[PDB]
Amino acid sequence: IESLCMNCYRNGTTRLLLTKIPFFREIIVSSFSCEHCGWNNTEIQSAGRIQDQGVRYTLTVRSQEDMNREVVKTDSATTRIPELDFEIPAFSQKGALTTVEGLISRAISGLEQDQPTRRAVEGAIAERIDEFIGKLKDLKQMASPFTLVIDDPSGNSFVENPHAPQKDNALVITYYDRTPQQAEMLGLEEDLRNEVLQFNTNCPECNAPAQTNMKLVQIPHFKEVIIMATNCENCGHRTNEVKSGGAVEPLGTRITLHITDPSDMTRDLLKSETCSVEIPELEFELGMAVLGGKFTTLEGLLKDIRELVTKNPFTLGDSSNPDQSEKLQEFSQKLGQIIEGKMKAHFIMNDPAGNSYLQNVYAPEDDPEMKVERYKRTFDQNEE
Ligand SMILES: [Zn+2]
Ligand SMILES: [Zn+2]
């Protein structure tokens, strides 16, 4: 973007850095620089996505000057030319910067480009389209004025006033309060969540410095947890552990997901160090401390499981060749099929401590294919 330098009055360069913020707002950073005199400046502006009021531009077109007017037309805007009973309804076209004449030329092209086909296969309809196209083309000869109406409930559409600071009598601009219909059509204060804050802290056994990574995880659809990942350099002590940070003493949780859709792959997923994972169709269960303490996705976990199991074969307790296991090859094939979306299976996460999460893509509503059972674990066979 070429912009005037206020320090030397040459043209320099403006870079625009845009940031989305919650609740239909945007920050625009305009960073100016001039290579010639070295001057530089930055302005930070905050903008709403939606204006307070809808806008309606009613332009009487009389001259080439009017035809040359720049037009910004948002996707939510309706366009009409009432003298031709013509309408481009909202959401027919994507947002665009054009001109008044450009608008009309694009409409002509939209009708005209397929007329060779239409004239061949639908003669009578094509004849009436040809007749309308001629009416649009006639507007460019400008023997009579016509009206262009652009009505946008978002308020973001724009029609240029080519008469500079002077008045623009040919263009009547009205503003209106949106109906609830208009508001809903547009998808109508702060979101200060901190989903993850991460820091190194002491070794929980040896008090060595900065040996444990601690992640405070505070997502909306799940209780606060702290993930601790140790890997000691001074003592060798290694552990991954998820702990509940809130008041609720967690019960056991058994989550059963029926995997029915490739979309299931992107479900978010925390597995704790006490969470067993089972895929009953594949006769497979993972140890509780395995491949977890990790915030991942279902696809991420399944691919990890595929690597662990099928890419690290061994034999313990017999003389069989670990690289020739029928059941391992069967497992690899079927897991691949689940990952690719070509096979349905149940995925069960069972955590007696309730420190594990699987995204419910229907939240806060129930997922028909996901069942969560809660239970109390009173007995530990390893000694409690
Ligand atoms: Zn300059
Ligand atoms: Zn240590």
Image: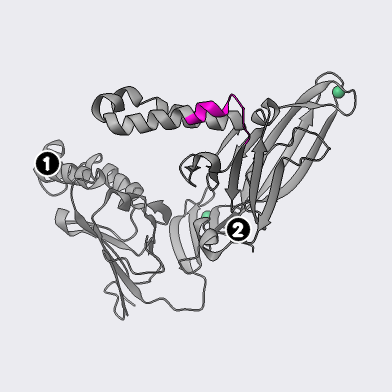
Residue at left offset 52%, top offset 71% = 245
Whether residue 207 is visible here, answered yes or no, is: yes
Q: Amino acid at mark 2?
A: Phe
The foreground one among 95 and 309 is 95
Front tag of 1 and 2: 2
Q: Earlier in the sequence, mark 1 or mark 2?
A: 2
Residue 264, horizontal then vertical, whole percent: 31, 53
Whether residue 99 is visible here, answered yes or no, is: no
Label 2, secondary structure: give it: loop
Determine if the magenta segment contains residue 327: no
| Magenta-drawn segment | 135-145
How many marks can you see? 2
Locate the C terminus and report the quarter of the image it occupies. Answer: bottom left
Q: Specify whether 298 is left or right of 214.
A: left
Residue 109, horizontal then vertical, whole percent: 45, 27
Q: Amino acid at mark 1?
A: Ser
Q: Specify whether 327 is left or right of 294.
A: left
Q: CA distance from mark 1 to mark 2?
A: 55 Å
